[PDB]
Image (tube, rainbow, N blue to C red):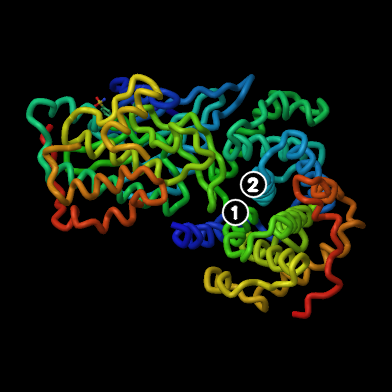
Amino acid sequence: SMENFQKVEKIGEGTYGVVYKARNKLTGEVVALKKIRLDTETEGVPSTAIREISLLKELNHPNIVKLLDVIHTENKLYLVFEFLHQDLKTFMDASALTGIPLPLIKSYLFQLLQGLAFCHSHRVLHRDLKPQNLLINTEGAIKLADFGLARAFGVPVRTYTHEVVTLWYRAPEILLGCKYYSTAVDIWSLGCIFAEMVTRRALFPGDSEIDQLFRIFRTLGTPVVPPLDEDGRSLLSQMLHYDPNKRISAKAALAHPFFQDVTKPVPHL
Amino acid sequence: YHEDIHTYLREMEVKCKPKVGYMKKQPDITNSMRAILVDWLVEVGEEYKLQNETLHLAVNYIDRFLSSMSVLRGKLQLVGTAAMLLASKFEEIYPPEVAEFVYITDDTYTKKQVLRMEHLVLKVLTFDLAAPTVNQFLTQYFLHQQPANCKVESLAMFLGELSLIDADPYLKYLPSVIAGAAFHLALYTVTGQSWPESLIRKTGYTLESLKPCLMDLHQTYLKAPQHAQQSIREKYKNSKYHGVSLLNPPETLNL
Ligand SMILES: NS(=O)(=O)c1ccc(Nc2nc(OCC3CCCCC3)c3nc[nH]c3n2)cc1
Ligand SMILES: [Mg+2]
């Protein structure tokens, strides 16, 4: 089963399981392996694994991480993914003193919205957009990862799980416990990440739910990013609109004048 | 994304479609046994207050599993139990725990059997669980009401559920078509309106193109009291669904 894979190093722990860097001994391919324990006497295959796998098998896009294989054993499930060289959070930290060039920020946002628009047009909400879950390679690409908190949504949506999105990236409609939420929640997260790429610090780093809400109302007003030009500010304000319906969709965001001159720069690693 | 999503589900319903003739290739089980199973699942869905979507998913999984795996009749309920458990994990905010599924089989099966079947079903379906359902198309169609009528919505939902019971004829029809026939019949029964213009534009389905499925579902509605399986009728008598099953079907459609 796993005979052909040599573990190189442990990468981290996401919503569930553990991710390792591994190499295929026969092809030379370097992969990320997600190891998933199965509760064989109690609860079985976790719902997070069921959702991530079923949905990732549908979502084939350049800006969504590729699931290559699922390896079954009696007691473990291993997901074989393409390996990306590092996460956006690590990149930003390494760039804390020198900053990230605007052409790169713009390219990254463009690609993320492409991946997100693909998700949303395929009735999938990600629900965990944070720089830790966004992976970059040495050739200018960025991709959506860790679909452990994702789900398939209905048209129209019904009430879904409230315990969703890390605090810092959580949209006002979640923080106020609105009955319904949808695709707008992911755009909010992306709006926060856009701001964080430009400053290299989190936009709304709340210490609690109330602190989170106050930080949002402080910055936006009751229902920002100096290095950013007029085109950038306009897009950012549309991604951080208070009203979920008024908040821009990923599709419409791609047609924004901010992206008129977007290229694909290679990052500095 | 309402149009993008609709298009995608129309594509997916073809890929996720079970084998039409499969029960003929099953040596130990029949359509009558599948009816018994699907009815019991309706009961399960009621005891645990599951989403209607969950029940529709569970049925898709069972039909697809039985399309490729021969199953003896003593193990048929085991397949169904595992399918409902998988659908619950996929769709529910708070799915019942495994022990609750073992309890409802009245201790015919062990918890180890249920969990081992869960894994077998995942393997056979190759984890492809995000299937389009009648319920999914219906929720979309309800948006084309003017005005919204929860008697109509509940009765379409009722008729859509009746189709799950009978593999013959309903295996040969797509979720989108069944949802089309159910919505027209519910709309007509309650108000007297027909399949809306805006829904033809959306779906490409006309009342003539929905006709064969409409004829079957019309008959299914008229003879529903005499069906061996009565759980869906009993469910839809409750004020939760506004007692839509207590209504009299139209004698005709004038199609
Ligand atoms: N920290 S880091 O900068 O040293 C570094 C980061 C991530 C990776 N690579 C990588 N990681 C994944 O998820 C692991 C990660 C995601 C969720 C949070 C915990 C763990 C993948 N999933 C498919 N392919 C993947 N590739 C390499 C180096
Ligand atoms: Mg047979």
Vertical side of B197 occupied by A261: above or below: above
Residue A249 position in % (x across, y down): 35, 52
> Distance of mark 1 from mark 2, alpha carbons?
7 Å
State whether discs 1 and 2 lie on one chain.
yes
The residue at the point 32 percent across, 20 percent down is A10
| Label 2 environment density (alpha carbons within 10 Å; few <14, some 14–19, many ≥20) | some
Please identify the quarter of the rendering in which residue A254 is found.
bottom left
Hey, what amino acid is under mark 2?
Glu
The residue at the point 48 percent across, 57 percent down is B5
- Residue A32 visible? The answer is yes
Disc 2: host chain: B
Q: Is residue A29 left or right of residue A67?
A: left
The residue at the point 65 percent across, 72 percent down is B195
Vertical side of B74 occupied by B18: above or below: below
Q: Earlier in the sequence, mark 1 or mark 2?
A: 2
Is the distance from the Cβ of mark 1 to the nearest ligand 1 atom less than 8 Å?
no
Q: Is residue B142 left or right of residue A21?
A: right
Hey, what amino acid is under mark 1?
Gln
Specify the farthest residue to the front: A222
Query: Circle 2 sits on which residue?
Result: B53
Query: Circle 1 sits on which residue?
Result: B136
Residue B138 position in % (x across, y down): 63, 58
Vertical side of B86 occupied by B98: above or below: above
Please identify the quarter of the rendering in which residue B169 is found.
bottom right
- The one of B17 and A71 positioned closer to us in this rendering: B17
Residue B96 is marked as none
Q: Is residue B220 left or right of residue A115?
A: right
Q: Determine whether label 1 and label 2 are within 8 Å by CB.
A: yes
- Residue B23 visible? The answer is no
